[PDB]
Image: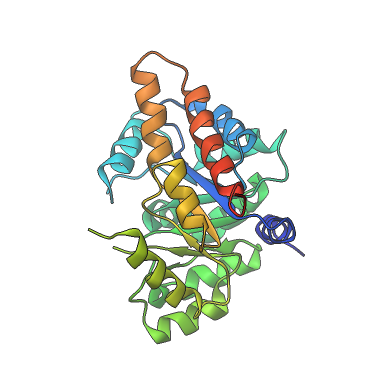
Amino acid sequence: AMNRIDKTLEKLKANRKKMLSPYITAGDPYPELTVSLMHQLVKSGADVLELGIPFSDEGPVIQRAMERALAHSIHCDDVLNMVRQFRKTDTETPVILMGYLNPIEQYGYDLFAQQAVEAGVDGTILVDLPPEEADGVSRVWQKHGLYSIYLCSPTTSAERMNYINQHANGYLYYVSLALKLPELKAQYLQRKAQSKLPLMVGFGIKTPEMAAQVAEFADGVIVGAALINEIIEAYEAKKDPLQASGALLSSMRQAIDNIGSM
């Protein structure tokens, strides 16, 4: 009874590699491109995919991405269908759905949980679900074997970390909301020492160089918006966003893997 996330994290650990996880919004810039983007990212070195559920509610880059997607009336079922299409040729790469609690609740907690797993979703990141309100979701998610990726920060309380260290599976999403790299490193390592699960840095990764500098000490890096910009700028410039996003992620994949060399 193993989740794709745990299997992937094990192979990474055995290969002495760090996780590289890209985020894109489902349906951005148009629906017919999402699955193609998912494959391209995996091809360019993505270990885990984060797929955003569009919702109107957070940085301006992600906000505009969700607005673009919502113009195509992209909803939960559409996101799940894209995962199914993806799973027709990719059954290995873990897929994480990222989004807000409201669309899932309107869909129905239990109905969404089983549909997500059936579609091939391995876990969720609920950005507006604090641990104090996650009891109900945690129980339903556990029934269908859906992982809950919890967030934590430099200020995450001791009681929260206790709750997180028990109910969280897979990995933790590290956030920290004029921050420089040395200060980040110190704060990250402090939090990592208090976490059972591996701690993935999920902000501020814009370039291959930065990705490599963070991966020096971090368990993994999450690309939060850099790929969104790369895709939409290539699209606006009448260029190919598949090549653009791939080239950016490949550059990060290579920079991360080149750690330890001379």
